[PDB]
Length: 69
DNA sequence: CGTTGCGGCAAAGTTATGGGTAAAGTCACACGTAGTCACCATAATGAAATAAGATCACTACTGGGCAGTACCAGACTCGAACTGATG
Image (tube, rainbow, N blue to C red):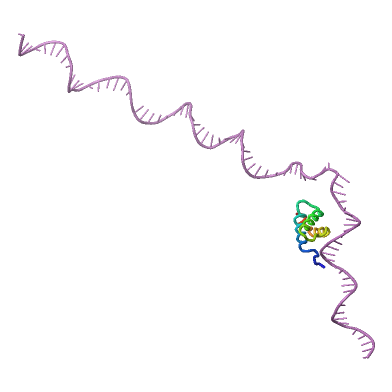
């Protein structure tokens, strides 16, 4: 079952937050960025992904680009 | 007719994949990361020096005029004397 179980708006928001609040010149930890994402999701009325989902997708962005950013 | 092998049908069984939730791990807080030669071109004087220029001193060459001399008359001026009118 490769179908994504999260709603599309939840994806888009979490993509945006991983892009613009984690890979940034601050070296923020994953817990704080997840908390900010959850706060934004609760403002937007969408489903907030769990912390394990955040860590797993962050683990999908590893390599050169993230280490450089 | 009965038996036997074969094949369709539809649960049922097995892997796989992307989610959530408690719970075992993981690791930094322990004063500390910035810090230091090496590098060769450009401005930038200040000195070193210029290359020509400026003036002195001497040597030789060549224009060339001034104080003084001299004659041949022409012409005005006037001693000295002559001579005529006169009161």
